[PDB]
Image (cartoon, rainbow, N blue to C red):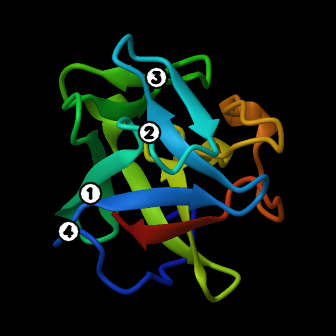
Amino acid sequence: HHHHFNLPPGNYKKPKLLYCSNGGHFLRILPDGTVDGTRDRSDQHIQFQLSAESVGEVYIKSTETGQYLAMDTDGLVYGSQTPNEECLFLERLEENHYNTYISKKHAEKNWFLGIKKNGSVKRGPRTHYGQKAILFLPLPV
């Protein structure tokens, strides 16, 4: 409805690292549910298992902790112990080669997952099409 349907080649079979090209950070969920970006390729909290719920709809789960990436009503990204509506993301291809993650619940507002150059995760409303912060590369673990 609100977005295009260009999809990235499949990437759920194996766990992946979600590399943000903006500042070169790996998405990370700390045990306390804190979400940020880290440049430390040796972190034990940057590995995720993605799975398709519906074509183009995914869940992003931390393999270390089992926490699910989610986005709250206020646009803040957090780690959810259990899967819910806030955990569904629209996985799309962007600029022909990257992956973008749009909050399903907030799809009409174009709220995305994105990381600033300083490694801080962005609030939903601060993100938008055209930004570098929303571009991810799923890398092998």
| Foreground: disc 4 or disc 1 | 4
Q: Position of residue 135 (x, y in %)?
A: 66, 64
* Structural distance between the alpha carbons of marks 2 and 1: 18 Å
SS for tag 4? loop
Residue named by callout 4: 14
Q: Is residue 130 left or right of residue 77?
A: right
Q: Are marks 2 and 1 in contact (CB under 8 Å)?
A: no
* Structural distance between the alpha carbons of marks 4 and 1: 8 Å
* Structural distance between the alpha carbons of marks 3 and 2: 18 Å
Circle on res. 90: none
| Foreground: disc 4 or disc 3 | 4
**Which badge, 4 or 1, comes first in the chain's sequence?**
4
Residue named by callout 3: 78
Circle on res. 43: 2
Circle on res. 50: 1
Q: Is residue 29 above or below residue 108?
A: above
Report the front residue among 131 and 16. 16
Query: Circle 1: is it few (<14), some (14-19), or many (20+) Cα within 10 Å?
Result: many
